[PDB]
Length: 105
Length: 108
Length: 110
Image (cartoon, rainbow over all chains, first blue to last red; front, side, top):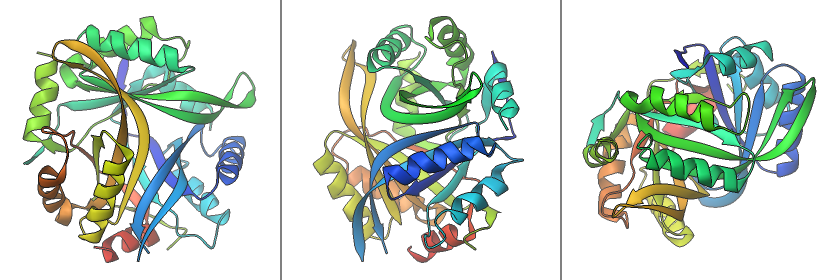
């Protein structure tokens, strides 16, 4: 059952292509910067004038210990870009999932 | 109108296929454990069984109250196709008065 | 600023759903035009809920409005005048960190 959590983090960022998204996910998990990553296609509307672009939403599961390192490494992979960077803190998790995630880093 | 909230919860998990996701969503709602469930197709990448895997999955977001969360999670665990399901819980910090009321009422 | 994470308390994500892609695109455009959000993202989903006593499953568009707490009230009030549903979903999350560069872009856009 559930345990209240303060040290888990979800890092949400965007990249332009699926190819990049698949590569970033794999190398992030390979490097121990995230335990898992999801990729979701989205359409974004934003001011840059108003642009409408199709991109990939990435959600990286990680801990507060690995977060700063993860965010920097991601930016090193597209240093020209000014990507979305938003982090959420879950208030709870299962014991088992929390332990797997921490063990994977 | 907007109101600060502390008793709403979004439980996030993933399942393999669309059928699995539809069945689990319907049954949670029918059990009165979630007010609504959203399902989004995703690709995931993770370490499992000593390897890095890339797979297509369905992201699920169960909208519920703190009162039903422990029950929903115990139920999920008995019903989930994965041995170790993803289980992450987010807390909204605000809602409309009318939406907050709708969620709570759906589970009353 | 691109490489540095900072704690944020002033950023907000407002989540709602609408029925059609046309609706979503029209709302997202108008929110950015009016300075109420810096960025709006749209994602196709399926949602399951009880309606008129029966379990319904419907295709919808999930929207995520990225904004500040200074604009959040105005956004929500504006949404209620412009949303196609009688009782729209409205859940707001607080990101607790961002990059210096993204937070500044977001603030400067509003």
